[PDB]
Amino acid sequence: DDGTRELRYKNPFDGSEITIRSPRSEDFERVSTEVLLLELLETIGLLLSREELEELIKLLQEEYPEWTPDQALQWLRDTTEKTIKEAAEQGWNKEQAFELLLSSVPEKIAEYLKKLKEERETDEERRKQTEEDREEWEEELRERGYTISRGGSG
Ligand SMILES: [K+]
Ligand SMILES: [K+]
């Protein structure tokens, strides 16, 4: 995509000009989908950071150069959601649902997911850091007016 919003105005009265830009990665469509996808992956036992999700976006674009960043993110979201649904329909546990996600993504994607998965399990310090960045980013979104409400069965 263009990747950057812009508003530009040239003042005919005093000759000044102002250029206002902001990346599309901070728009609600991108942000809310990223919050959703991190919640989705945690449901099947994978705690990731935003920056690691951005990394999955880049690798996906390398597998499919025609895909935009938004396109790759939505495909990851949909693939994760359809993995959630099929796991709920088959009565699988979190590990089986995670295996289905690995077999639904390209080889380079799955190897990066398994690396991060192993890292969260073997490195307790970095896992706590991942959770720390997750709550920090949520608090930063709440400072911007975001409301993130969780309510389930359990
Ligand atoms: K890339
Ligand atoms: K799937």
Image (cartoon, rainbow, N blue to C red):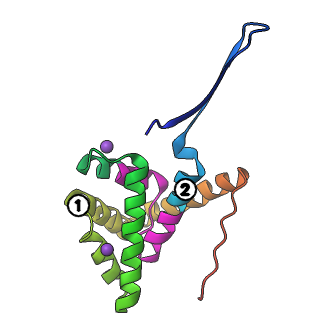
Quadrant holding ligand 1? Answer: top left
Q: Which residues are magenta?
A: 36-57
Q: Secondary structure at mark 2?
A: helix
Pair 1/2: label in front = 1
Instruction: State the residue position of label 1.
Output: 106
| Along the viewing direction, whichever of 67 and 32 lies nearer the viewer | 67
Residue 110 location, x and y as percent? 26, 64
User: Main structural element of the magenta stretch: helix, strand or loop?
Assistant: helix
Q: Which residue is mark 2?
A: 133
Q: Is 152 placed above or below 30 here?
A: below
**Residue 30 can be seen in this image:** yes
Q: Is residue 52 visible to the viewer in this orientation of the structure?
A: no
Residue 35 percent across, percent down from the top left = 54, 61
Q: Residue at x 27, y 59 (%)?
A: 109
Q: Is residue 109 shown left or right of residue 138?
A: left
**Position of 84 compared to 23: left or right?**
left
